[PDB]
Amino acid sequence: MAAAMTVKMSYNGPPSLEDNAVHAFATTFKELVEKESGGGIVIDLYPNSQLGNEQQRMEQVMTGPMINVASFGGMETVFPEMFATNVPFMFESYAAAHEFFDNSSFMDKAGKELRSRTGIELLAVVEEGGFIAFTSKKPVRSPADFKGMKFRAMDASQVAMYEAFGASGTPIPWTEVYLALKTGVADGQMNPPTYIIIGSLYEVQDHLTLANVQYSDQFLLINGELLDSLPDSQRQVIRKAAHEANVKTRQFVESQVDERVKFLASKGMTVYTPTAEELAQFKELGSPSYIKWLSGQIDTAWIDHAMEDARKANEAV
Ligand SMILES: [Cl-]
């Protein structure tokens, strides 16, 4: 009888079920796909960006039968339109973002476009941290404080935001962020507490700013030629399992966000929550600059459509 379908799955960070939201997602996803497909599909897990940096894994998922969990560092290479979903302060809550990423017509449209353009199918927008925070060696309270500073960027949109705040941005691969921050190349970076913990960044950063500037997510990608080659019941399994692992990983992320900040404090990290006025400054200077930069990379219709669907999601909840 025909062999079971073995499908490789690539993603960032260590295989700890306790700290890496993406590893928790993969683990649950593997179990559900195998249970639901009755052994017909087998998911082999490749943690730690083992098989390559963001751009490399994007190449791989486009050319070969596999799964990749990509960050914006990978997504920007073939689909910068997805940046439209990533405007600072776009979502007022985890519920709003879930509503947008699960139901909005933007995501239907973005999904079809990505598939026809790249041969990749988007299965889930994976929440893998709370709202993004800033780290640094010096206190950061407002955009004012960014003047003169060197920040690590994950993607070109992060570069753009730093600049708007008066700092410089430098793309550094995730696996090299600790190095960059210690050897002076960068003073700060942005991430939810999950990644600050998994990268042990508290050793080379001692200020944490809870600006909640962006929704933290990554992207479950599958080679579309693979997915389409599977019998219908196997395709639905992968899709249903992707959503089911997502709703469980969302609980994993959201219910531990306070204890993760508490943890960072106990590792010497001075934690700072911006005042309402300082937030409003982060937004009035951060959102319009972000959209102006993005307008020069993609058709603005994507921006209009994303802002509109975000407004509807914020209001629908
Ligand atoms: Cl978090």
Image (cartoon, rainbow, N blue to C red):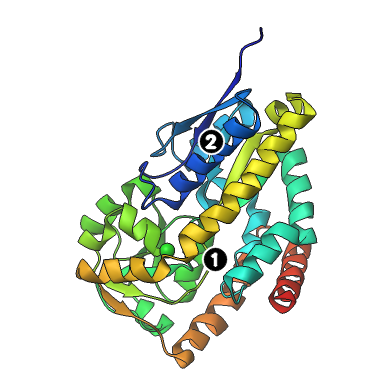
**Viewer-nearest residue: 204 or 125:** 125
281 w.r.t. 233: above or below = below
Task: Name the quarter where the C terminus is drawn.
Answer: bottom right
Task: Name the quarter where the N terminus is drawn.
Answer: top right
User: The disc labelled 2 sits on which kind of residue?
Assistant: Lys
Residue drawn at x 74%, y 37% is 236
Return the residue at label 2: 30
Residue drawn at x 65%, y 29% is 37
Q: 10 Å neighbourhood of mark 1: few (<14), some, or many (≥20)?
A: many
> Which of the two discs, 2 and 1, labels the residue nearer the N terminus?
2
Question: How far apart, in angstroms, are the residues tagged by discs 2 and 1?
Answer: 25 Å
**Viewer-nearest residue: 40 or 270:** 40
Q: Looking at the picture, how far across and down is residue 17, in whole percent?
A: 39, 47
Taking the view exactly as shown, the residue that stands out farthest to the bottom is 277
Task: Nearest to the eye among marks 2 and 1: give it.
Answer: 2
**Viewer-nearest residue: 278 or 288:** 278
Q: Secondary structure at mark 1?
A: loop
> Of the numbered discs in the image, which one, if any, rests on residue 215?
1
Q: Looking at the picture, how far across and down is residue 84, in whole percent?
A: 66, 63
**Viewer-nearest residue: 187 or 97:** 97
User: The disc labelled 1 sits on which kind of residue?
Assistant: Tyr
Answer with the quadrant where ligand 1 appears in the image.
Answer: bottom left
Q: How many marks?
A: 2
Q: Looking at the picture, how far across and down is residue 126, in whole percent?
A: 57, 52
Q: 10 Å neighbourhood of mark 2: few (<14), some, or many (≥20)?
A: many
Residue drawn at x 65%, y 71% is 96
